[PDB]
Image 1 (cartoon, rainbow, N blue to C red):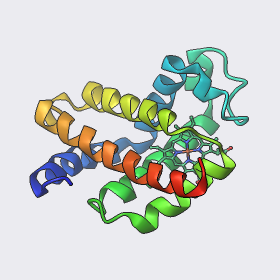
Image 2 (image 1 turned 30 degrees about the vertical axis):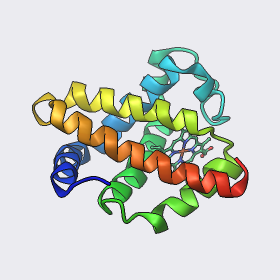
Image 3 (image 1 turned 60 degrees about the vertical axis):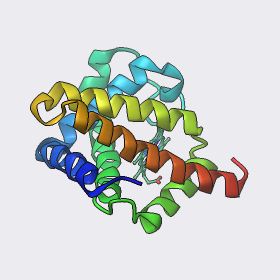
Length: 151
Ligand code: HEM
């Protein structure tokens, strides 16, 4: 369970992210795809992209980065009381998109890296640890839903 202090650190940096949702979403998905190419293969929508420049030039990829970070932001602002937001996401990601929990770990790493690059003064080690805990909570709770469903 995150403390109130930990949530403050998470949401303080997240308020910075929200000044440029789409740029962050692009950097995070690109980092995910470059670092873990099996992830790109899960997107029929993106698997034609073969270079980082092609990824950066895709408006559809940028739109999807906004979709992703908008959903994550709504979850983080619930400070753990996020059951209603996570159910539909876990259901789609387990049963329709067929995303393993491990790939959620990979996107969490990409998020943390991009936040560190873009917001170092609001993303020192205390805030990195708190965000790690927030994303771990996200993963834990999705994984319990996956287990229920047999994924
Ligand atoms: C922070 C983690 C993530 C969040 C918040 C997130 C959120 C979303 C949202 C809101 C959608 C659209 C609604 C829905 O289908 O549920 C979506 C679609 C999708 N997500 Fe994620 N997602 C995450 C991680 C991932 C990862 C790691 C993968 C793949 C490796 C993935 C693959 C997909 C796919 C394939 C779709 C459908 C895209 C399309 O063809 O339009 N998601 N995601």
